[PDB]
Length: 75
Image 1 (tube, one colour):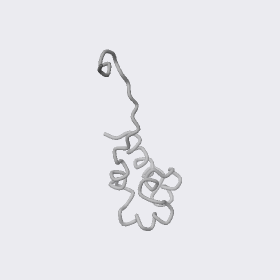
Image 2: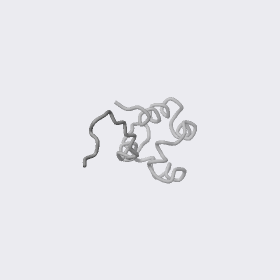
Image 3: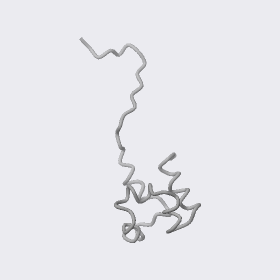
């Protein structure tokens, strides 16, 4: 009795790779601005993953875009 290795298996796994720790390393967020932005955002995970509008408030629309795009699709 084995787990069937016969066949192609797709497994969408809910495994958060600790993106939140990398999300605070994004240029434009600002580790110094973190406690100030922490007044708006509960923690770094909501912080950098905040909507463009909220991120634009502290930096700019395009800066927000690079941050928000970063975790959406990185390389």
